[PDB]
Image: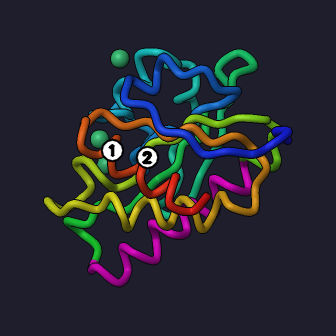
Amino acid sequence: GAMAPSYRVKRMDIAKNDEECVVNAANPRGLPGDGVCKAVYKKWPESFKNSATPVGTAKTVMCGTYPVIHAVGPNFSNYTESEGDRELAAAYREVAKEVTRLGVNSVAIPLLSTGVYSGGKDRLTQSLNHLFTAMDSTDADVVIYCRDKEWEKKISEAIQMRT
Ligand SMILES: [Cl-]
Ligand SMILES: [Cl-]
Ligand SMILES: [Cl-]
């Protein structure tokens, strides 16, 4: 575990992370996709061998020795708000099980279901609060990746407000 487990946020491409493993915002079919998924496919294409997995689950595939945790959040265009909320919480719980199983001291993580799976809504708080619910009982250092300057500020505020 980390000596003093922490949360941090950085505004940059998760493909350039400085952590011991990465969480992909995957689709259920293991396809290259869009957004974070496409960046992950460019950097770690070997990790897409047999990565298909259902909504609400995570599946780890190694790229060399570097673990890629493919986490499938719901697409809110298809799910009801209630069922999508349940599956988004479930995907993060499965990320926490994998991070623990792998024994890593740090993990790079995007906010699941916030981009093209957001159903056109701002889901920063919903997705971040499910991340915290799952990861709070882990001892890995967690580094959240985002691309928007205003999101960086709001994620940073949410972290700092709990310390
Ligand atoms: Cl960048
Ligand atoms: Cl998304
Ligand atoms: Cl963002």
Residue 82: give x, y in percent of width and height.
Answer: 35, 84
Q: Are marks 1 and 2 in contact (CB under 8 Å)?
A: yes
Instruction: Say few, some or many: other residues with alpha carbon within 10 Å of mark 2 (under 14 / 14 to 19 / 20 or more).
Output: some
Q: Residue at x 55, y 68 (%)?
A: 90
62 to 26, vertically: above or below:
above
Extreme residue in the bottom direction: 82
What is the secondary structure assignment of the residue under circle 1?
Answer: helix
What is the secondary structure assignment of the residue under circle 2?
Answer: helix
Per the rendered image, the range of residues in magenta is 80-98
Q: Residue at x 14, y 59 (%)?
A: 120
Residue 95: give x, y in percent of width and height.
Answer: 63, 53
Q: Residue at x 38, y 24 (%)?
A: 12
Q: Residue at x 37, y 30 (%)?
A: 11
Q: Looking at mark 1, is its residue's CB closer than 8 Å to ligand 3?
A: no
Image quarter hosting the C terminus: bottom right
Residue 122: give x, y in percent of width and height.
Answer: 21, 60
Residue 149: give x, y in percent of width and height.
Answer: 25, 36
Instruction: Say few, some or many: other residues with alpha carbon within 10 Å of mark 1 (under 14 / 14 to 19 / 20 or more).
Output: few
Image quarter hosting the N terminus: top right
Q: Quadrant of residue 136?
A: bottom right
Amino acid type of disc 2?
A: Ser
In-image side of 115 versus 56 (left or right): left
Extreme residue in the left direction: 120
Dot 1 corresponds to which residue?
A: 153
Q: Main secondary structure of the magenta part?
A: helix
Dot 2 corresponds to which residue?
A: 156
Residue 18 is one of the magenta-drawn residues = no
43 to 68, vertically: above or below:
above
Amino acid type of disc 1?
A: Lys
